[PDB]
Amino acid sequence: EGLGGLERFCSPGKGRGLRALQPFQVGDLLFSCPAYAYVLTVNERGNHCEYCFTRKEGLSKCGRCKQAFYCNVECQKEDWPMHKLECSPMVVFGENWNPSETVRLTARILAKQKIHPERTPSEKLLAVKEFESHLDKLDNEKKDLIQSDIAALHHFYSKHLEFPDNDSLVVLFAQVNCNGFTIEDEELSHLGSAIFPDVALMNHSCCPNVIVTYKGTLAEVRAVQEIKPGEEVFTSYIDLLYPTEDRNDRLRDSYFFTCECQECTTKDKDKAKVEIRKLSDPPKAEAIRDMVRYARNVIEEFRRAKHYKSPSELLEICELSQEKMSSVFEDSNVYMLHMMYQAMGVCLYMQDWEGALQYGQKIIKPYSKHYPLYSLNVASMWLKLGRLYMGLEHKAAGEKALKKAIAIMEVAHGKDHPYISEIKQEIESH
Ligand SMILES: Nc1ncnc2c1ncn2[C@@H]1O[C@H](CSCC[C@H](N)C(=O)O)[C@@H](O)[C@H]1O
Ligand code: NI
Ligand code: NI
Ligand SMILES: [Zn+2]
Ligand SMILES: [Zn+2]
Ligand SMILES: [Zn+2]
């Protein structure tokens, strides 16, 4: 089956890719991909529906496990062939049931291949079986991690799946690591993980021409730039706030390729991204190389500390790190912004609304200067600052920030996306 107005071609040096045949304007929808296989992240059960992802109050709990909710019984029955892979296992394993989301999603992919071997509507251009794996590029540490996931798959999903051999399972796992998507809500909060075959056919660019948004469990690809007939459709696979070197470190590590787009070539946004303090005695080169090294290393240590250190301690880390950095860097620097965004999140947990709003206010502007025009990160930030304002009863400011969020969202999600009608109703109440 073909996908209208688009075409799968051979992108030189980028393997298989998707190009446009007709023109697409900013905001236009390229295509929609129903999810081939998906799973709702554990920290969201009860909040969202396990079948359609609809966010609602009062959802039908599952009688057997009491850990899976639905809007009604049609969603419960419709989700059974997939939920049964964990209902009983969740009750029998109890506190020992902790498969990694990657393992859960892969189990669902195996169940899907068994129930529907034929090509699905989610595979009109690219098929799950023909996914790029990058297995020959794997080293021993990465092969060891894929081995731990195969051990988890067998350990938790043996009641129903018919596993092939380790050769086939390390391939599928490499394929999921290369083409698996993560679903986020209107605030970029993680909801789940899914497999979107046709969507996984678009290569990466740091200057993307399309954004992927989700309408429930449906992928929607909308043009954020003008796409002319014959030019490739490009998506951003990573967080575009960081400098070139950081971006490619993530691209090479996770996707086995070194981007070459205009941005990675000329590195225009790099300067402002690593703004140095216009001091009287401007910092020395080696001082900057040393500060970038320290910053990158503390990013990693904070990722590690978020797993056992109390919020007070984490906040102390963002403050002390921002202290030591503020001597070479400007607050617009992406490393100061990183520590600040993390601090704002910690305040959001502690329910220190005013502290979270203060940090947000400080972050938003540089955030706009660093990301593209239509960026889901910028929109979700405006959305968060807007709901912070409205919660605290700052109607004027909340209305301004919310309007900014709807500005970008109308392009990315389309003007009729339920998220937008929801924010508009959010403006008509406080
Ligand atoms: N800009 C780019 N430069 C080189 N390779 C790219 C690229 N963008 C995507 N890729 C390749 O695309 C894979 C992502 S899945 C995207 C489609 C892929 N080209 C395929 O034929 O199946 C990456 O692992 C990498 O191999
Ligand atoms: Ni996770
Ligand atoms: Ni991706
Ligand atoms: Zn539902
Ligand atoms: Zn259940
Ligand atoms: Zn790039």
Image: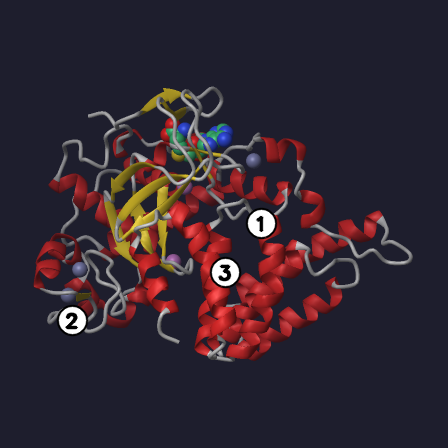
Q: In the image, what residue type sits under mark 2?
A: Lys
Residue 381 image label:
3
Residue 31 in picture, x, y percent from top left: 30, 36
For the view shown, which residue lies furthest in the right direction? Answer: 281
Q: Earlier in the sequence, mark 2 or mark 3?
A: 2
Figure quadrant, ligand 4:
bottom left
Residue at horizontal 19%, vertical 73%?
58
Its colouring scheme is secondary structure
Q: Is mark 3 within 8 Å of ligand 3?
A: no
**Percent coordinates x, y for residue 325 in the rendering:** 73, 62
Front one among 27 and 97: 27
Q: Give the amino acid type for the residue marked by disc 3 in the picture.
A: Met
- Position of 110 with respect to 103 (left or right) is left
Label 2 Cα neighbours within 10 Å, binned few <14 / some 14-19 / many ≥20: some
Instruction: Let me know if residue 209 appears in the view.
Output: yes
Instruction: From the image, tell me which residue sits under label 1.
Output: 241
The part of the image, by quadrant, that contains residue 104 is: bottom left
Mark 1 vs mark 2, foreground winner is 1
Q: In terms of depth relative to the viewer, which is nearer, 312 or 185?
A: 185
Q: Earlier in the sequence, mark 1 or mark 3?
A: 1
**CB under 8 Å between discs 2 and 3:** no
